[PDB]
Length: 49
DNA sequence: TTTTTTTTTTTTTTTTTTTTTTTTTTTTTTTTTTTTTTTTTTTTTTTTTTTTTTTTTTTTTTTTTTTTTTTTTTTTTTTTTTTTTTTTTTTTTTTTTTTTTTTTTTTTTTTTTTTTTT
Image 1 (cartoon, rainbow, N blue to C red):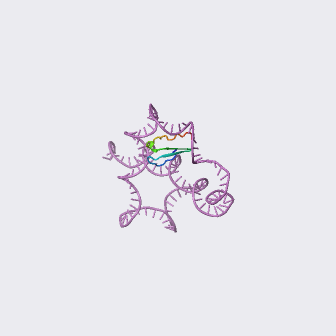
Image 2: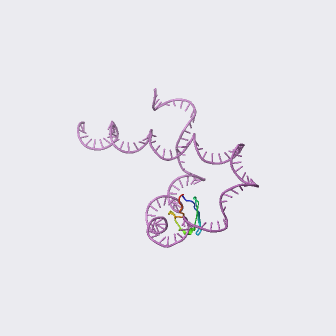
Image 3: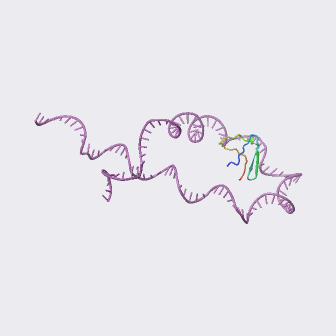
């Protein structure tokens, strides 16, 4: 499913919150400007559940 | 004066078509059955002061495994093309307004005759 969707601008740092006690931060500018009906880019090597 | 040719509507009854009585399938419609909303009050739940012993964060230091890292080659991403769907101009058709032209039906009442059934 889709975890959550927020509307953001360039150079705004985004954080994740795993349900197995994890939190990460990657500048949003690192990742390429995606398009519709495409695949996805990995973010977090979240092992297990 | 007798006798000879031709013309059509009827004895027609049968073939073709039309008209008129019929009853399977998807679209309506009334019923029962399950989702919603407002009150009473009711034990019951729940909001807020005081005290208390607790158990997790912050002085300080340690390491190691996730954060550094560079690079090969994949493969998702993007490009062009074409098909399918959505949506809006365009057109067509139909309805209502008020003076005109035309029509068409259902029943009482009595008395007499046809026209079927028993």
